[PDB]
Image (tube, coloured by chain):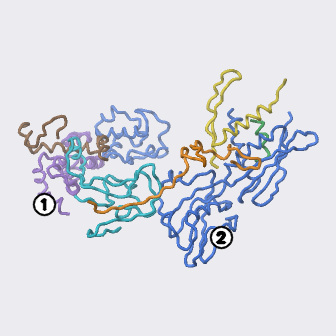
Chain colours: A purple, B orange, C blue, D green, E yellow, F brown, G cyan
Amino acid sequence: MSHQKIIQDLIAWIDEHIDQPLNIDVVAKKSGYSKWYLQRMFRTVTHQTLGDYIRQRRLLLAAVELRTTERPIFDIAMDLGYVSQQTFSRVFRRQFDRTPSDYRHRL
Amino acid sequence: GVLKIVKVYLAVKRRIQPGDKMAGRHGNKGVISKINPIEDMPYDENGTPV
Amino acid sequence: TEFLKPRLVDIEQVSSTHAKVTLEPLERGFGHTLGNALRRILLSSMPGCAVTEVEIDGVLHEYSTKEGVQEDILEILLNLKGLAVRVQGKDEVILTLNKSGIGPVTAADITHDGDVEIVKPQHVICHLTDENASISMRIKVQRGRGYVPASTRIHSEEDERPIGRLLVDACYSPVERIAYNVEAARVEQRTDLDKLVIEMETNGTIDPEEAIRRAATILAEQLEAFVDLRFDPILLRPVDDLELTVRSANCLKAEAIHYIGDLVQRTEVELLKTPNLGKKSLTEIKDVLASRGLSLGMRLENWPPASIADE
Amino acid sequence: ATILAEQLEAFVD
Amino acid sequence: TEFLKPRLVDIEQVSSTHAKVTLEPLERGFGHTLGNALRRILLSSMPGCA
Amino acid sequence: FGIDMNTDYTLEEVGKQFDTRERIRQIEAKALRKLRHPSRSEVLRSFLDD
Amino acid sequence: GPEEITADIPNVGEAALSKLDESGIVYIGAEVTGGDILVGKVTPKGETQLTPEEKLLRAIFGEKASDVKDSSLRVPNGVSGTVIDVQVFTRDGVEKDKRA
């Protein structure tokens, strides 16, 4: 069909299983086309990239998950997609402009 | 050793069940064996049961 | 054959409380047969309107006191159990009763409606000796049968009530006393016939024919055993309004499935082998089949309605 | 049963 | 009116004339009444020859 | 956590063996997730009514 | 630690907490059934560890621990009726509570 609907059928798909440790190969699986083409076909519909929105959606959940759980900050990193909490605060403080522990406690 | 003691009376009303003890007034003991609907009890020629 | 039909002949009342009714004629030896039968029906099983629920101001539990009255409250609850009322059409009534002034408490002082028939106007309930104290009660009257002793209902119906609804035991019997006598019916060709004398002693609220009549409706129904005998809402929908796993509704319409009847036949070997679904999708595809109780590939009766819906 | 049922026809109607 | 209606449960017909017939359940105080109906109306009223 | 053993190691106690101290606890986070996602916790939520 | 009486009781649903006051004493005139509560009494649980099956199980759903162990009075079973009178005994010097 038309490719603008197909990406709008794929925009929700990543956003619906945000809890999983999902990678790009499962995303190109639903595409039915190649992995490089979905890097272009998502860009040529959304005017917004895919390979950063996979991280941004888990940062959109980091607006919620760091506001909901009193569980330690070292644990929340891998379900966002990083093997290091140090890398988690590496991509937090550039984006949401704080240390992430001050995101939980300042209400 | 006590701090405070709350003490509550509650009241229960107990009905006849098959197996309360019963007696006359000469010492004949008794256990109530069955409660019976009014139909098949004996009754007299005028129409009262017993 | 030598059959004969018994006809209801006379109804005569001694008082309004006490009445007799003859039945004529029964056949040979049938006197005790129908007499002892009808005695066992009228003792237990006639409908009557009794008092089941009392509720009254200034009362926190049953065994308290109340100022200005002679009796105690469970003597009161023992007293109005013998108060008789006739209800005509309503399945359930609510009365009202307010009173003050020094003197005895009647029953006719209640503000009864046009359809509410009290019987005994001199049945004393309470003794108000101080005019400053008043009585203020509401009496829930029902209609039922048997001897439900007010406790098995609250062991069964646990809809939570506040404090103050005082329960009292129902005596649904309208009948208190019944006997029969067997006399000899004269018809000048059949001198073996026997006429019946059936006594009834009761309160009001009884038509003396209906008690005999509704008893005959009981035996008429309880003898049939000896003469006669010896769509699911989410199944008519597409995948789009299934409200399932997060990434299943937007993707199941991508593989020609826009009904749930179209979904309950689709295979577990090749739907997941065309790369447009996920691995967490088949498990809740299975929930639409398992929680409803179907199998894989089961062809169904008539799935498509007039509306075929997709975007 | 037809003996008892026919014996009680006159009270139901 | 909260009566009941049973169904004929079993006829273990042993011979052409010997059989037990069971019937349950009823509202209480009728098994005597149906029986004491059928005890007398059957044994003392039925046509036949001799 | 000591199931089916008798030694109860800490972060430094297997991290001197395997190769890691920053990824030891962190891999339990998806061992949390699909387990705390109620697809397997049917045998685990039942015991938390204690 | 000192015990006390309050209706905030652990491991209780809405049904047993249906008919109490703020202070865990039944209203004068409620109905009762064996298996329910009259006094809400709680004790300081002494900190004892357990066999470590529950310990990771505490770490799965985030089980909040309690220093609040139930030792309240419950109605003896087979007994079902109405409560008609209460009264409260309290020392002199301790602050007299709400129901006091």
In the displayed structure, would residue C219 be above or below residue C64?
A: above
User: What is the three-letter code of the residue carrying label 1?
Assistant: Arg
* Quarter of the image with the N terminus of chain C in it: top right
Q: Residue at the location (10% across, 45% down)?
A: F22
Q: Position of residue G55 (x, y in %)?
A: 21, 44
Task: Say which chain tag 1 marks.
Answer: A
Q: Residue flagged by tag 2: what amino acid is it?
A: Thr
Relative side of B13 to A103, left or right: right
Observer-nearest of A52 and D11: D11
What is the CA distance from the residue labelled 2 to the residue labelled 1? 82 Å
Instruction: Name the residue at the right extreme.
Output: C188
Nearest the eye: C81 or A103: C81
Give coordinates of residue C119: x percent, y percent: 70, 64
* x and y, in percent, of residue C142 in the image: 61, 58
The answer to which of F31 and C189 lies nearer the viewer is: C189
Q: Which mark is residue C106?
A: 2
Helix, strand or loop at label 1? It is: loop
Q: Chain of mark 2?
A: C
Q: With E47 as the anchor, is C245 left or right in this view? A: left
Q: Residues within 10 Å of mark 2 (few under 14, many from 20)?
A: some
| Residue furthest to the left | F16
Q: What SS does tag 2 mark?
A: loop
User: Is disc 2 in the same subunit as disc 1?
Assistant: no
Name the residue that disc number 1 marks.
A98
Q: Residue at x 81, y 48 (%)?
A: C197
State how many labels appear: 2
- Residue C286's tag is none
Packing grade of label 1 (10 A; few <14, some 14-19, many >=20) is few
C21 w.r.t. C295: above or below:
below
